[PDB]
Image (cartoon, coloured by chain):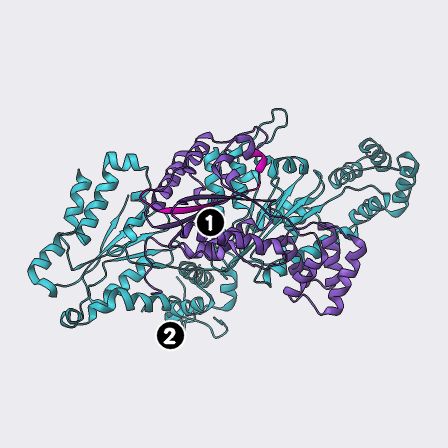
Amino acid sequence: LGVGGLDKEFTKIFRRAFASRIFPPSVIEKLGISHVKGLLLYGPPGTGKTLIARKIGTMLNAKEPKIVNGPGSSEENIRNLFKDAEAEYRAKGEESSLHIIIFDELDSVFKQRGSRGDGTGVGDNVVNQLLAKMDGVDQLNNILVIGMTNRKDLIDSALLRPGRFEVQVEIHLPDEKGRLQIFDIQTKKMRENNMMSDDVNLKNFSGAEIEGLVKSASSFAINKTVNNTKDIAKLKVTREDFLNALNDVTPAFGISEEDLKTCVEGGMMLYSERVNSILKNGARYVRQVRESDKSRLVSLLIHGPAGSGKTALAAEIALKSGFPFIRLISPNELSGMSESAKIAYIDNTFRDAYKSPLNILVIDSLETLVDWVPIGPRFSNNILQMLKVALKRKPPQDRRLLIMTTTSAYSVLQQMDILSCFDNEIAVPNMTNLDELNNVMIESNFLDDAGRVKVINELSRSCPNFNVGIKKTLTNIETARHDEDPVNELVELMTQSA
Amino acid sequence: LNDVTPAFGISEEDLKTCVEGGMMLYSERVNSILKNGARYVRQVRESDKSRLVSLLIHGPAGSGKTALAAEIALKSGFPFIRLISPNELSGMSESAKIAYIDNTFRDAYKSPLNILVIDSLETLVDWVPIGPRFSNNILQMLKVALKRKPPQDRRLLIMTTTSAYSVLQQMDILSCFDNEIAVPNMTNLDELNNVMIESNFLDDAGRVKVINELSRSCPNFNVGIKKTLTNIETARHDEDPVNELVELMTQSA
């Protein structure tokens, strides 16, 4: 006990890796089987793997586990590790006590080119000695080796065949019931020492985050009294302290709120029906993904001219969805990186997207991310291939995600023949009528109606056929306003723009 | 049995789950193609003259090709079946890719009967037409590999898929393949009616109306199955399903 939310895996592990040890050697001999000698654990960091290893070791009452970190002396160390198990085995035969050895960051051994690993021998030698110690003719029957890695795919298949690492297990991010149990475990002592109020009533957090939250709540409670004083005995934490604590702990695996909110919106205003149509289609394509089991990967292409509003729309659709996981890939993230670094970053983002039931990603200005210059033309083909492959793969184990991407260079993409990745295309047009200008002026409180009327009347025959984006109109109102004559300055600016 | 998985075998999950999310016989050509595939399979399995066979499946993108290849493979019953696709080679240097292909080919030569599927050949070589840019070493490796015969009275079958017939014709590697298969798109409203029926879209009264509207909105449409099965799915969730699927299908057409 001391672990929460992981009952099923505990049952499985106890059933297979340990249960044969509880029984006397006589009955196991009488059946004709042999104990398992390898177990592989994998999952994200800080989730409770070493915790399980240690707590299991207490039930069998084996010796305190040895622990080793992967990253001539190295050749000599491995033989030093097993000494005690050899001694105890010669000492007491099959009845010797159990010896448990923990190995961390196993993949680091393999994470090198084969040529260097074998020529230096550092990578290969440890592996060969270790396999020799549990499979070969010097087999020791008292040992069990636990391996731990965040990436299973890099371990060679030779290790996974029977006799070596036969059983493999995955660790997940906890669910709500797990967190409720953790809340109870963490608040037990507060609750049982009358230091927790009666109003406290116990999304993607881990255990450490709950510990930090409780500590922050305590910090609020402790701060309110200091500046050491009388009446310490009346201390109690309260719901408001927790709700204040929620504003100080921000989780990993979440929503990049600030970038979308501040950077991508400095206004949003419904000057025509087409915007409403687009927003409706987005809410339909959001709850489609959220309420259908056939659609677990959607891709869309919000296209239109430069300066039209695209990204602000995308973000606006994103914010209203409420999914737990949301992210965006834009040029700003990749500035100053080499090509390989960019590829690694993209791939890591994609890995991170594959560990939640729901996920959203936004990709902005694709033709800029590819370094397109039409004079050459010049562009990096590798990034294009990476993205083209990644834009079709579907998440594993009944998860689902939605991808929105934006571009202003439709013909170039068409000419690159990567238009088969998208399920739908949207067009964002500019402004071409004075009614739209009237709406914008009214919405921005430019000045009293009489002048707005005069401006419209003047433009009626000064320039009746204009064609301009929102950005320039909203930077022309601003400069005209802080001018002596805002109506002649705005008229002049606008006719110049037209 | 559901707890111990052997090395050497069939990569069941990849073929089954990835490559097939529907299969419905909406025309005679599909039946004919499947019959031809079965013919070839039991040809290889019941003759000593044919110990290496190679096939080419081609047609427009999104047509159904890969799902067909998988369907022919799963029904074969051979002990050894594998597929090479871009997903496996992603993130590798050219040398690693070539070595992986070579290891696969060696592993194919160690059982009486074997099947291999190669998907999207033009992407494995990294073709882009602006240059054009591509890798020639992988091309020559593949070209040589498609003619070598397995040793010691063993036999295998190869199926490859492509959408860039003109490019392969230009690159002069059509002599590796023994036969070519063509896959067309849907072109009649009867097939669409069948698909709606097959997917329980809605009661006949409304199902009829969309057909009656397409009758004089767009009688000569050309759309693949995948899009149609994602347009039924999105239109079903609309508030006005008939007008949504007809507008969306007209746009696609």
Q: The purple chain is which one?
A: B
Which residue is depicted at the point 18% across and 71% down? A31
Give coordinates of residue A369: x percent, y percent. 57, 36
Q: Chain A is drawn in which colour?
A: cyan
The residue indicated by pointer 1 is: A351
Name which residue type carries label 2.
Answer: Glu
Assign a secondary structure to mark 1: helix
Image quadrant occupied by the N terminus of chain B: bottom left
Give coordinates of residue A318: x percent, y percent. 62, 53
Q: Which of marks 1 and 2 is nearer the N terminus?
A: 2
The residue indicated by pointer 2 is: A192
The answer, for residue A44, to whether it is visible in the render is yes
Assign a secondary structure to mark 2: helix
The residue stretch that appears in magenta: B151-167
The answer, for residue A232, to whether it is visible in the render is no
Q: How crowded is mark 1: few (under 14 residues within 10 Å), some or many (20 or more)?
A: few
Which residue is depicted at the point 63% across and 64% down? B198
Direction from residue A77 to residue B115 in the image, left or right = right
Name which residue type carries label 1.
Answer: Arg
* Chain that bears disc 1: A
Which residue is depicted at the point 60% across and 26% down? A377
Q: Are marks 1 and 2 on the same chain?
A: yes
Direction from residue A368 to residue B107 in the image, left or right = left
Residue extending furthest left?
A91
